[PDB]
Length: 492
Ligand SMILES: *C(=O)[C@@H](NC(=O)Cc1cccs1)[C@@H]1NC(C(=O)O)=C(/C=C/c2ccc([N+](=O)[O-])cc2[N+](=O)[O-])CS1
Image (cartoon, rainbow, N blue to C red; front, side, top):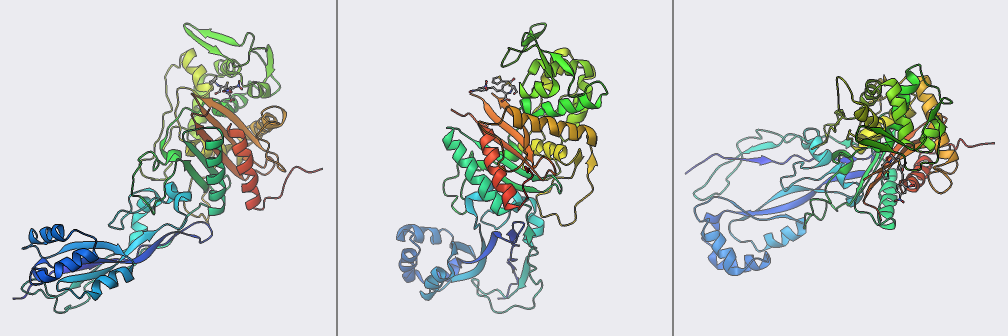
């Protein structure tokens, strides 16, 4: 005669904004439609009109209901515009009930899909920040006490057992303005250079905040009809790649810290090749004998960096790379994030020392490389990575000594000004610094920070299988510094 079950009360799921309160993920009211089959079986004359008004086949609908005859409840349609749901309600069919419900909407859409992520039909995070802060955002579902009837008639509620608690607002470190800039210029380059996938990260070197993270290809999380698993891949967090020549600045920092190297010291790279048993280190352009250390970067000499590494040892280079976070957990707690590989030897071989010095044998994510570069721009100080707005900045760790870090910044500044600039990479108005890298078709890498005299932004551009990165960097950096009203530092 009487039965007491418990239908839960959906919590309003917390708003996600960028730095500036711009909505990135919003709980939209919608309407589900369910029905008591036992109620529906007393109204079989009504089913064809209900099927029709649900776009479901008359005889399939009937079958669906017949074979759920003894079951108390089923879902008709989830997530109609409340009016669409209201029209179905007008039909006033016995047994057809509604529940109001929240469905997430993503106003920035594809622009920031990998960072924000998306929910599943339960309104429960299943990628990105939506999944990473699902606690914070979800809030406590309330519960209803009510009275059963012979086939599912609700009579009343005994008491409000649980008031539903809303989830909490979440403001990201992303600046949707810089995010849009990066999204756009990255996508142009992919097309302009005939390339397959991309990534671009922008970090605030002072606060640890990720200002922008974008990837190509990307998807529209509002329209997930055809899945395309490659498009949803948040590469900046997930693709480990080998970083190549963009770790030569940390090799160099190890050298300048050893006590044995200053930038005007000389290495002989004649003839542009070097052997270790069967392994042969090749430079890309081999018309050099003596180079100074700024020159080994400007001429992108693998032989020169390996010769410095042999003198100082791989252990020193490994230690600098580990202190900046290469191949180390970032603590972001983002879903399926990859740690990467930093190889360790008790006795490093000459071949293994050479490859590590020039970026091979280790694998990193773009977030790690950006973070390492941010540690270089802030003068050797690593502020912890953050994907949420940082109003009170945590203390940073000194991982490279400031004189050495300041010295490395200058060499990188000379890398952009004398050669590695004039065709691409010079950021107009500000002194920029950075290092290019080429990873096998190949993968095009560029990492750097700006402005050179009070560094603010660190940036990584990763572009795969092109038919390169330095313009993407130069353009995105230019606009990013302007969006932040960073006064130019290239002055008379
Ligand atoms: C660091 O990664 C070094 N590269 C290698 O040792 C591995 C190589 C990949 C392909 C060739 S060698 C140095 N880094 C750089 C760099 O700083 O970008 C280069 C650049 C060489 C390069 C690559 C591709 C093309 N291209 O038009 O396709 C042209 C050049 N190039 O300018 O000669 C490699 S050495």
